[PDB]
Image (tube, rainbow, N blue to C red):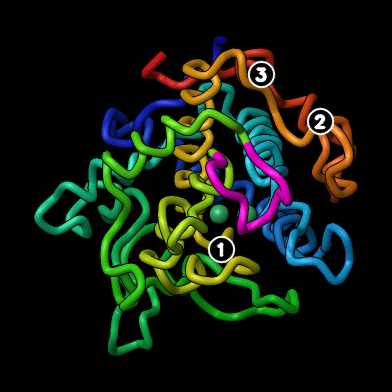
Amino acid sequence: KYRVRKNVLHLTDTEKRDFVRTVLILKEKGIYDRYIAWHGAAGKFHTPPGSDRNAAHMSSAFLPWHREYLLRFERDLQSINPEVTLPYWEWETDAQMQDPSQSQIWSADFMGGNGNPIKDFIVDTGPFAAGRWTTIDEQGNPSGGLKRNFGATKEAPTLPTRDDVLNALKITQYDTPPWDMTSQNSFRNQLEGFINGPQLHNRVHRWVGGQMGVGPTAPNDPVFFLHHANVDRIWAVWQIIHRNQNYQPMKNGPFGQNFRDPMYPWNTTPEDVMNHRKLGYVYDIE
Ligand SMILES: [Cu+2]
Ligand SMILES: [Cu+2]
């Protein structure tokens, strides 16, 4: 309840400067790379093998997986700078703008801007511009630059709306069998965005483009964590609202998806991260 995750737009220039600096440090130290690989590994871990579901996506573990993932990242920032916490990108408000790409999150002192269509959508502004920040491909080999291409996709010309987010918060069950991308009247499948996809979470990735367009390379873009911080806030808000609801499946789901299963690549369980306050953080909106 001490660490407070703030909205990006409420950040002081110094806070924004300190977040970036710490992320750059994690990168230099070789720590940042551990996160990208954990994510890649996870999406490759199929539950069960042959199934669509994996440890980190397309099933019930989606929400807790990333919560643990973000918890570990924040602790790592914290080891560098005890004053630094993970902010969130409230994409639903930016979506209200005439031109969302005009959001302050993309300023040169923070995330940097859109991709340069002359350099194949390589990002050349900001702290994470090519030549300042090295990227890795799916194979673990250098890929040579952050790429972004906002709203370029026919399927996802726009970010998700405030109404889209409110409509997910109305769903009663955390998830429903068969605990996959076809799960109906499920908050998890809804938020993840497979209901008439891409919506919500999935929709943000498609809208951002570049590495953020494809799962395995998503975290190469530091905006990945800001986005997942916002996703985690929505879940946390749901938990407050539907407080007689609990995680599902409690059992009989596939191994890795149940309440008390370890979440590959770690030993952490969904039970372990069910209460975010217990983890030592809370979002501003409280
Ligand atoms: Cu993920
Ligand atoms: Cu994601």
Q: Residue furthest left?
A: 98
| Cβ of mark 1 under 8 A from ligand 2 | yes
Q: Which amino acid, mark 3?
A: Asn
Neighbours of disc 3 within 10 Å: few (<14), some (14-19), many (20+): some
Q: Quadrant of residue 41?
A: bottom right
User: Of the residues tagged 2 and 1, which is closer to the observer?
Assistant: 2
Secondary structure found at label 1:
helix
Mark earlier in primary sequence (1, 3): 1
| Cβ of mark 2 under 8 A from ligand 1 | no
Q: Is residue 130 left or right of residue 258?
A: left
Whether residue 76 is visible to the viewer of this picture, yes or no, is: no
Which residue was labeled with disc 2?
250
Q: Which residues are magenta?
A: 175-186
Q: Could you tell me which residue is drawn at 46 percent across and 47 percent down?
A: 227
Residue 148 position, x and y percent, is: 38, 71
Residue 134 position, x and y percent, is: 57, 70
Secondary structure found at label 2:
loop
Q: Is residue 265 left or right of residue 37?
A: right
Which residue was labeled with disc 1?
218
Q: Could you tell me which residue is drawn at 66 percent across and 46 percent down?
A: 62
Which residue was labeled with disc 3?
275
